[PDB]
Length: 496
Ligand SMILES: CCCCCCCC/C=C/CCCCCCCC(=O)OC[C@H](O)CO
Ligand SMILES: CCCCCCCC/C=C/CCCCCCCC(=O)OC[C@H](O)CO
Ligand SMILES: CCCCCCCC/C=C/CCCCCCCC(=O)OC[C@H](O)CO
Image 1 (cartoon, rainbow, N blue to C red):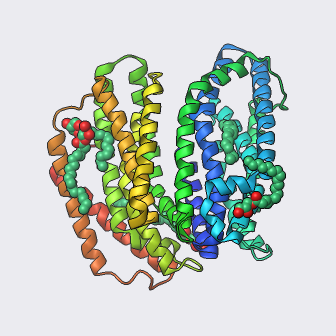
Image 2: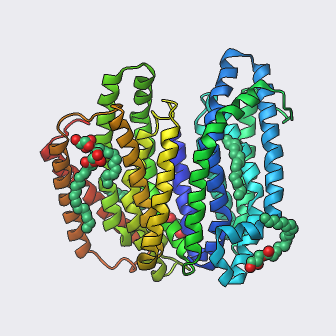
Image 3: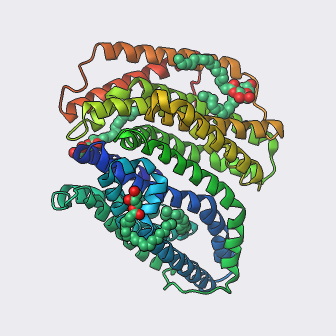
């Protein structure tokens, strides 16, 4: 369900990314678009996922299960109304203050004033999407409360489609061509909304928004939002300051980081969705029922699974950074220089894939423990270490150093959450990790050896059509995966 539609969305997101790279490359225009659209949406996502979504899903289901459909319709009406009012005000203030928002977020764009102007213009086109995508994600949250998961998963396909179409059709018309993306995004917003509204009507939860300050449920969802806003703020501030750092770097830095991060995202989302259906449900159940012993059992199996699957992915992405970048991005305005810079950023990002997967495996269980004080402390530490690693790595490695900083920060964040579990006896690993790690290390050595060998005997990656390059890429990915799994088979792990 989710596993099929959210990954169709994934190839279309990656296809739109390749289209962007092909048509606009990695430079001033693409830098401006990323700071203008991606950075505000990421702040918005952090806020909604960290505070609004966490508060909204329990209260909504609690209405749905303990009160009628009419009471739930009224709750949803007042929630969507207050959301729309706040976001309309927020959007209006943002379009007015856009030059100051770009100045604070990306100070270094001021050196090319025309680039700063495009970033401001694109934020003005972009900003209405915040409203649209928030309404669409509220729709999707409601539908998920009604156990309809495939529609909200498929919904971002419409954004990807809209952006691809705006690039292919509207870009030559638009006077700065990447302006077209904005409108695609805009159309995308509307489409993502329009697609989900009838399904909402299907469950009788499509209702005209309405404003009130007396609703008990609205104040409940406002109260559970409170303690999470400090951590949301930490994460937002860190991301803002990272962008500030990158803004002083050479044009394309933001775009190179973006492309590397998407390349690196690609398998990590697969693994995250897959472990979120194999492991997290049973972990949540074990924590809710108070079964400590078998919670440890799953925690250990899941951490071993993380080492078994995220490590080979990270190392393979590092070894295959040029194959991947050249085969998936190096067309049109994406030059060979852009490909090298993206390769470096991708090698840097590979360090933190492990930290990402483990943060997603450990963080469920703290929000369930209702311990937010120690994660907000961990988040402040992660901020401090991130900004410090930025100062340290920016001069020597530039954008790659900023990517290394983000990666190592994710590593330390996961490590600190694990240390909190270890100190409070929340988790203690099972015996036999040592020989298990040795098995991994041998299998990784075999995999990397086979990959290096093949690459020495395989053509220059720039040479060929996209069919040819992606065929070669898939051939080496297959040989590497096969060889890693064959080394593992000799060691053991015959069944899961
Ligand atoms: C927190 C600040 C709140 C400010 C509220 C202002 C309300 C009126 C806004 C007009 C925008 C239209 C004009 C857009 C260009 C303004 C020039 C500017 O400030 O640009 C930055 C500068 O270029 C860097 O070097
Ligand atoms: C153990 C191994 C771990 C590493 C695993 C690495 C996976 C590499 C696969 C990539 C295929 C996914 C991307 C598919 C891209 C389709 C082609 C495309 O993007 O075409 C756009 C073009 O510009 C239109 O004009
Ligand atoms: C050139 C770049 C260098 C490439 C790398 C060379 C290999 C270095 C050695 C690895 C041992 C790793 C040991 C740790 C692995 C499992 C994690 C662990 O033990 O964590 C304990 C936890 O922190 C509770 O305090």
